[PDB]
Image (cartoon, rainbow, N blue to C red; front, side, top):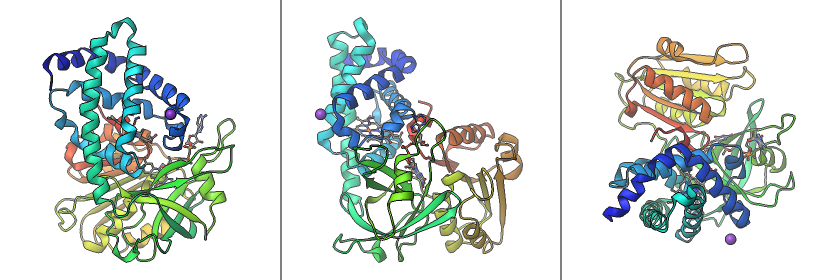
Length: 398
Ligand SMILES: Cc1cc2nc3c(=O)[nH]c(=O)nc-3n(C[C@H](O)[C@H](O)[C@H](O)COP(=O)(O)OP(=O)(O)OC[C@H]3O[C@@H](n4cnc5c(N)ncnc54)[C@H](O)[C@@H]3O)c2cc1C
Ligand code: HEM
Ligand SMILES: O=N[O-]
Ligand SMILES: [K+]
């Protein structure tokens, strides 16, 4: 809607494409300096030293390039919406983001941002914001339970030298029944914690993938310890969960979220193989999926490709071997990067079939590298699914 508006928006594509991240960095710095209450929601680390500014810049760019038809973006809007919904973002949060976005645009564009250009962006923001609010309302409706609910930590077990699997059960009166919780392998939960070390003053929200779609004996997720290396601090919430949150303590969770999921129609057939490709703690939702595959159809050709620094840091070794031993047609491919090369294109060409249903998960950089290889091996987009442990929109070409 609005024809002169849409040309104005399009005329800013070049600045967003080349300077978009100057805009988004200014945005975060101003909004969070001026509005420290949002530090209870935004992950300081992703913006100051992570890829959050690139995720936003790419999304704003995609919206500007598709201003005539925003429906093109719906898969990205749903992906982001699942995170917003898990984080408890509501309609009444949207106007402040719009204020600060328009202000960052004005600041960066300078004399190249007249009132008409700003007005148009206000209009574009309203239309884009209305879409997200709508998707998210649906997600609030479908959520398995409402808002943050209290769980008790019932177990904490090392699944590698530096990865701890948490088992959580809902506190009685949370209205949550473990036997009546349909999980799709690939989903993550979100914790709302308030770490006490490092002079922390804010809540800290983090996503952790579910290790299993079985819930009867509690929900399970695994946290890698982001330890302190001379200079930079230990990861705030991973440290808090490893060292401070004991068995018996309460932790707050919002309901399972996310669009990462194994293709349900391909589970039960044998012609199309499954490739599960992980790095480090990225293994966690892939274990969930391997579990589902093996329980539903153990005859499917499966390729388990798992990279880690070394054997002690390789997570779920016994678990994975036991699941794999049940499969009649499996290749297990383990990489240890302390000695062995980082998985490259030739490795993938040699160790996995040309036409496969591929699910890959790990750090944003590992995802960027692996997608680049899978595209270079001519895999079709619709057979590559991935979940970066960070902002997915920083991994997408717009
Ligand atoms: C969909 C999704 C699923 C995820 N699933 C999992 C999972 O299953 N398991 C898991 O362990 N994680 C998972 N994550 C990542 C997880 O949510 C957290 O981001 C992770 O635990 C790190 O959080 P933290 O608070 O411990 O570290 P943060 O305090 O946010 O710090 C993050 C990293 O930055 C470093 N750092 C801090 N300050 C600086 C600085 N000044 N300069 C340079 N570096 C710095 C820290 O040491 C740490 O390594 C997932 C993320 C997403 C988006
Ligand atoms: C139309 C408006 C909005 C857009 C276009 C947008 C866009 C995005 C994008 C691209 C991401 C990163 C997700 C990913 O790449 O995986 C994100 C995450 C996030 N968004 Fe929004 N968002 C909007 C509204 C809001 C509002 C109103 C708030 C709250 C005030 C909010 C809070 C957050 C938070 C807390 C995260 C997680 C940040 C992190 O993980 O570091 N968003 N959003
Ligand atoms: O970065 N605003 O989601
Ligand atoms: K404020």
